[PDB]
Length: 66
Image (cartoon, rainbow, N blue to C red; front, side, top):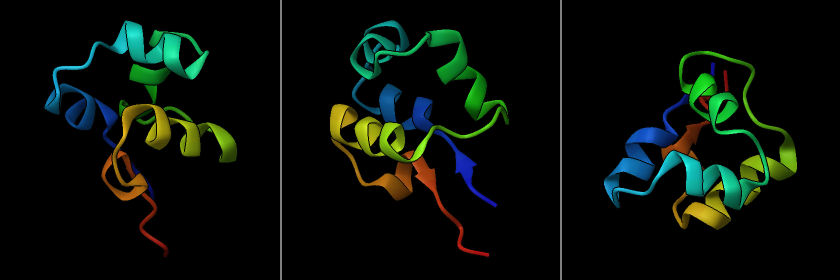
């Protein structure tokens, strides 16, 4: 389904997971865990990630509407 790949998006600007996680208000381990296939971020949080990260939601988490 949804492909979690913030790190690519974040690392695009060389954004730190730690700072980003601070931006998200969530633990870094969890955020980097999601790419690894851990349960994707919540409805608002994904929106926040796009907002905090400043990137389309699709790039960070391509919904892949199956």
